[PDB]
Amino acid sequence: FCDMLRLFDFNKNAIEKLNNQTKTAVNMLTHSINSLISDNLLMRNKLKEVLKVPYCNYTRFWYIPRCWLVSNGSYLNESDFRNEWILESDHLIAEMLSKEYQ
Amino acid sequence: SEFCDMLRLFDFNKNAIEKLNNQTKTAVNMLTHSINSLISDNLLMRNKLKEVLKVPYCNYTRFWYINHTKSGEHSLPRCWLVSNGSYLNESDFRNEWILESDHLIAEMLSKEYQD
Amino acid sequence: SEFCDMLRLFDFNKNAIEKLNNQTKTAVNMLTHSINSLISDNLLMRNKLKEVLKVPYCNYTRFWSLPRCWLVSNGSYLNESDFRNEWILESDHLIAEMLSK
Ligand SMILES: *[C@@H]1O[C@H](CO)[C@@H](O[C@@H]2O[C@H](CO)[C@@H](O[C@@H]3O[C@H](CO[C@H]4O[C@H](CO[C@H]5O[C@H](CO)[C@@H](O)[C@H](O)[C@@H]5O)[C@@H](O)[C@H](O[C@H]5O[C@H](CO)[C@@H](O)[C@H](O)[C@@H]5O)[C@@H]4O)[C@@H](O)[C@H](O[C@H]4O[C@H](CO)[C@@H](O)[C@H](O)[C@@H]4O)[C@@H]3O)[C@H](O)[C@H]2NC(C)=O)[C@H](O)[C@H]1NC(C)=O
Ligand SMILES: *[C@@H]1O[C@H](CO)[C@@H](O[C@@H]2O[C@H](CO)[C@@H](O[C@@H]3O[C@H](CO[C@H]4O[C@H](CO[C@H]5O[C@H](CO)[C@@H](O)[C@H](O)[C@@H]5O)[C@@H](O)[C@H](O[C@H]5O[C@H](CO)[C@@H](O)[C@H](O)[C@@H]5O)[C@@H]4O)[C@@H](O)[C@H](O[C@H]4O[C@H](CO)[C@@H](O)[C@H](O)[C@@H]4O)[C@@H]3O)[C@H](O)[C@H]2NC(C)=O)[C@H](O)[C@H]1NC(C)=O
Ligand SMILES: *[C@@H]1O[C@H](CO)[C@@H](O[C@@H]2O[C@H](CO)[C@@H](O[C@@H]3O[C@H](CO[C@H]4O[C@H](CO[C@H]5O[C@H](CO)[C@@H](O)[C@H](O)[C@@H]5O)[C@@H](O)[C@H](O[C@H]5O[C@H](CO)[C@@H](O)[C@H](O)[C@@H]5O)[C@@H]4O)[C@@H](O)[C@H](O[C@H]4O[C@H](CO)[C@@H](O)[C@H](O)[C@@H]4O)[C@@H]3O)[C@H](O)[C@H]2NC(C)=O)[C@H](O)[C@H]1NC(C)=O
Ligand SMILES: *[C@@H]1O[C@H](CO)[C@@H](O[C@@H]2O[C@H](CO)[C@@H](O[C@@H]3O[C@H](CO)[C@@H](O)[C@H](O)[C@@H]3O)[C@H](O)[C@H]2NC(C)=O)[C@H](O)[C@H]1NC(C)=O
Ligand SMILES: *[C@@H]1O[C@H](CO)[C@@H](O[C@@H]2O[C@H](CO)[C@@H](O)[C@H](O)[C@H]2NC(C)=O)[C@H](O)[C@H]1NC(C)=O
Ligand SMILES: *[C@@H]1O[C@H](CO)[C@@H](O)[C@H](O)[C@H]1NC(C)=O
Ligand SMILES: *[C@@H]1O[C@H](CO)[C@@H](O)[C@H](O)[C@H]1NC(C)=O
Ligand SMILES: *[C@@H]1O[C@H](CO)[C@@H](O)[C@H](O)[C@H]1NC(C)=O
Image (cartoon, rainbow over all chains, first blue to last red; front, side, top):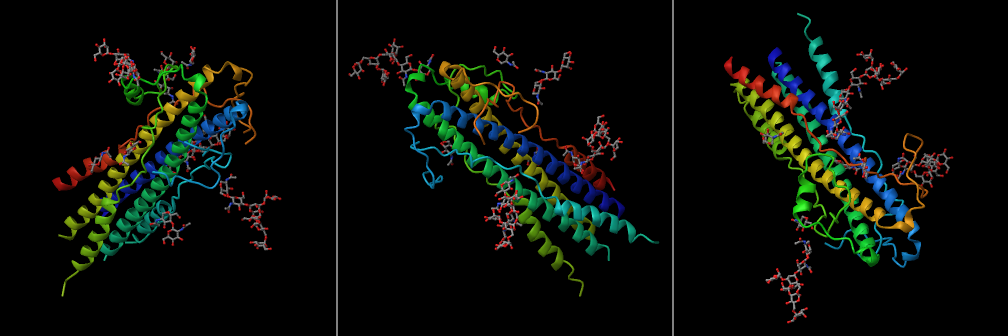
């Protein structure tokens, strides 16, 4: 019983570490991409005489370039990962340990 | 007894992995689409500032190395790395094991057979 | 019997996390490499347009839209994402031990 709780605990901790790693990775990538968006918009605004180029406005990636896709609405918001199940597993471990009243 | 509690613990872990898979898929796909939009705009810029096309494209050996140099790369501007071949395809996370876990739960419950 | 079935359930979860780790590493590394290529091309553009020399580089730190100052530099390149398999490796070692019982 104790060995099986340990196996569950390993899996649960491995998932936590992966969640942390993915959160760190995505947030690092998101911030880097946002910096590229900002610089690309800054370039566009300073080669203003080249703005014969229109903005796409409503169109997305239907077409599997003729207009700008990136706007000040393109910035990615930080991706905060939901640890709801991991937190419930932590609470379940505390409970599992309590039923031990023998 | 205790068997049912251990199935519940497995179920929590399985569901947590499923949610993380979904979250990572959503994140990657969102990032991919945003990066593809940046590629498109950068290519569109390049095509309209034809007086900047004294700049050559990376002679695939250069390009392969830049994508394989498992570091923060030297890169110091030399030729174009981004082409219409740089677009990222959507990321499809393979819930292979989670789907098999769901099928394993149905089996575990059947193997309670005992009369 | 039920012990062997519970080890199999743990094994499924452990392998599912493994596969996800592999997938995320592949995805992030692919994204990182693509973003690094965009950084390089954007810097290459900046270096070949002397008419944009007026544009300053950002005074880094905190306090971060309105167009002003370069954010991307040769210090912006992302390093490859090393996905540690610490727990998975320990689980693999624990399985070998469980089987010895
Ligand atoms: C991966 O997943 C796990 C699962 O949850 C996640 O969990 C983390 O677990 C670690 C282990 O403890 C947690 O670490 C703690 O973080 C505390 C947060 O403090 C922050 O803010 C501090 C404020 O600054 C002022 O106050 C501090 C004193 O509080 C003072 O020293 C400063 O000078 C300043 O006046 C800041 O200091 C702190 O920075 C760290 O480094 C400095 C450098 O020396 C040190 O002086 C600090 O004390 C601190 O260590 C940080 O930015 C932190 O306070 C805490 O430190 C004390 O308490 C812990 C116990 O709680 C003791 O073990 C430790 O020895 C210290 O006495 C400790 O560092 C972490 O917060 C958990 N995170 C979450 C989300 O729960 C991991 O983080 C995940 N990994 C990821 C995402 O990468
Ligand atoms: C990353 O991206 C995401 C994607 O959008 C982004 O999400 C947005 O987050 C912002 C907040 O940061 C959301 O907007 C805020 O909502 C606050 C909540 O107040 C609400 O209740 C008000 C009460 O009205 C009542 O009566 C009416 C009927 O008469 C009824 O319909 C209402 O439901 C309610 O019962 C309501 O008036 C108010 O309305 C605002 O928001 C709605 C959309 O939710 C919009 O349609 C309205 O036109 C109006 O803007 C709202 O429903 C609100 O207090 C807050 O206000 C800010 O601005 C005012 C000045 O305009 C300041 O005085 C105030 O202090 C706040 O600064 C703001 O509107 C927004 O809706 C989210 N987006 C979506 C799609 O939901 C994240 O934030 C991003 N991350 C960032 C930025 O870090
Ligand atoms: C980094 O990447 C870039 C990206 O491509 C790469 O650029 C290429 O550079 C190579 C040269 O190194 C280019 O190819 C060379 O072009 C030489 C020029 O000769 C031309 O004129 C010939 C005359 O024909 C006339 O009549 C015909 C109609 O009949 C008419 O169309 C012609 O325009 C012209 O009026 C013509 O025959 C010849 O054709 C070759 O090139 C074209 C493409 O330009 C191709 O479509 C043909 O099939 C044919 O290959 C050309 O237009 C040419 O002399 C040279 O030849 C080499 O090979 C022969 C043997 O086949 C050797 O005998 C000779 O000594 C040379 O070694 C070669 O073809 C290539 O076109 C560039 N790419 C592009 C898109 O333009 C850089 O080189 C890369 N950096 C590196 C490799 O370091
Ligand atoms: C991205 O990857 C590069 C590749 O290594 C990381 O660079 C490394 O950063 C460390 C941090 O200082 C350098 O260490 C230094 O070594 C000298 C040598 O004795 C020592 O005197 C210093 O006190 C320090 O220990 C390391 O040399 C350097 N390596 C290279 C090739 O640059 C970089 O930090 C990574 N960036 C990240 C993860 O954000
Ligand atoms: C993956 O994440 C998405 C993002 O919300 C979840 O979306 C929900 O999907 C359920 C399934 O029908 C809907 O009922 C909800 O209304 C959706 N929510 C939103 C905001 O769209 C999705 O369920 C997650 N995958 C899971 C839990 O398996
Ligand atoms: C993957 O993306 C590249 C980039 O353009 C594309 O050429 C290739 O066909 C894509 N693979 C697919 C859609 O299977
Ligand atoms: C990749 O997936 C396989 C499939 O189970 C797994 O055995 C292997 O350890 C994984 N590699 C990782 C997570 O680095
Ligand atoms: C950025 O490029 C310049 C140009 O030579 C170089 O001097 C500088 O050291 C580079 N930044 C690095 C290597 O971090």
